[PDB]
Length: 230
Length: 230
Ligand SMILES: NC(=O)c1ccc[n+]([C@@H]2O[C@H](COP(=O)([O-])OP(=O)(O)OC[C@H]3O[C@@H](n4cnc5c(N)ncnc54)[C@H](O)[C@@H]3O)[C@@H](O)[C@H]2O)c1
Ligand SMILES: Cc1cc2nc3c(=O)[nH]c(=O)nc-3n(C[C@@H](O)[C@H](O)[C@@H](O)COP(=O)(O)O)c2cc1C
Ligand SMILES: Cc1cc2nc3c(=O)[nH]c(=O)nc-3n(C[C@@H](O)[C@H](O)[C@@H](O)COP(=O)(O)O)c2cc1C
Image 1 (cartoon, helix red, strand yellow):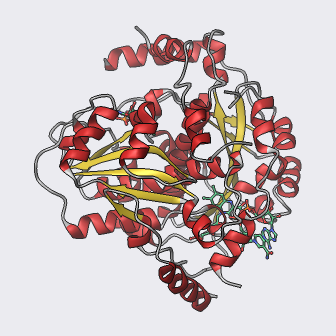
Image 2 (cartoon, chains in turn green, yellow):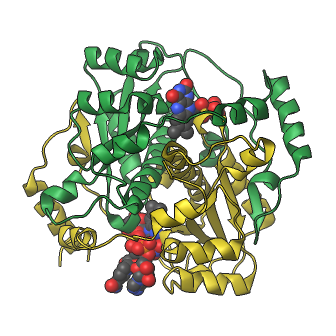
């Protein structure tokens, strides 16, 4: 079917044309996101649509100077939002890490619905997690209140490039039957060879990155917004 | 198009027939999940397919006695996995909260691709966050190693019920233009009335839950597996 064909045809698009996305298309992309499952129907995700050209420029910089953030027809910012709940009832305790996990999982689910909806319409896109490296600055720029935090952005627009589909680790490595199975390094070597043909190896790159520090300011940032304190 | 139609027709299915999911369908569902975007191409998600009936029963109880966990044709458990990286390179530091956020977000993205793929085939499903009630016990049952943790499960199978689509908060409440906008309590009251018509109110129910403690054992659990320690 068309749904599975769209899912399997995915590839991040980082170059867009100037052709805008229609109001009908955008509204449909948003409705698709809303139709996503929500943990306990809490609906803890907020989307900040950035149309202001100056804020776009600042966000492109806060993302690590990723130009496509400014050139994209649309730029959405996904945030954890327990402020809605806090406004309704001030007795809400939103500092439990469980709630941050829910915000993160539910955001990914919603964002993927938005992306797939866009892709099925012939649009291209890419997630922007780089915003987290400048979390505090991005948070202030968008005026996020207490019990709210930024997770990632998303570029949407008409493609101006046609990249090849990137191969993933094989299903037998990712999927485990009944119990977690030990990793067979021979599978990793085969994957590295596969990735080399596509393009330092994959395994060397990803593990080298994790060998150092991974944005140590993240927990302090979440805590400053009153999240993940216990 | 068909993709958008499938997305908008979503409703959680909690009643399944005894008809199993074919190998071809399951493989396609997994392939759809693998086609999802990955943060820095880290591929930090692992899926544990539970075919053991004795384990299914225990998981059903651990999930809060949710019967459909046992009756579902397929039950997939999504986990954060940095053990693959740790096996390749022992110098990997996987305790940074940033890495747990990446795991949670990426899991949601992958899982949604799996669900949509299934739903497009005429199948039904429901996320199972209830596994977190007994996270530590579910972890030991599945034999998850260090740098790995359980997030949620997913029931899949042929539907034996036809629930009506649940309405979400209006787009103007969830979507903010350029900056975070203050909540208009009138919109929440309107939504409550909409939910009452579908069926205490929604706002009263969700905030009442958040007024209590939300799975306080979660952070300690993550820490016990070497995650979210700093
Ligand atoms: N009737 C109740 O008091 C009650 C309470 C909680 C959830 N629910 C129902 O469970 C599902 C909600 O899942 P969630 O997104 O909140 O996830 P979740 O992760 O909170 O899992 C459901 C939790 O609610 C408990 N529960 C109590 N009655 C339940 C019931 N009749 N069916 C299933 N679980 C029940 C379970 O033990 C479990 O801890 C919905 O179908 C909802 O209608 C009902
Ligand atoms: C939550 C998340 C954040 C991401 N952040 C970035 C980012 O900041 N910039 C970028 O160019 N790509 C980012 N990516 C996307 C890609 O790196 C991408 O998914 C890729 O490595 C796999 O290729 P494909 O998406 O083309 O299949 C992100 C992916 C996810 C899931
Ligand atoms: C990550 C996640 C976990 C969830 N956990 C459960 C669960 O344990 N049990 C259940 O019956 N429903 C669960 N739900 C699904 C429903 O609560 C559901 O999304 C619902 O409240 C909204 O209705 P719909 O999905 O039918 O549109 C979960 C949803 C998500 C996103």
